[PDB]
Length: 21
Length: 48
Image (cartoon, rainbow over all chains, first blue to last red; front, top):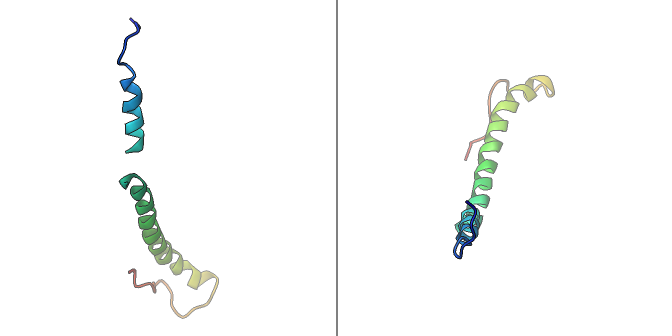
């Protein structure tokens, strides 16, 4: 299941934004 | 920057409410147990 891909980084930005609000 | 405002604002509320609560509660017993003050089972604070 855990294949690599370009784009998953978004999860890091989603978590950083949730933290700051 | 509401993030930091929310933190400090909540503190401001806690300050306001906490003082009123402890004043109204503790006064009832302090003036009966530690100092024989004429007032008993009554508050003093205008609660502004």
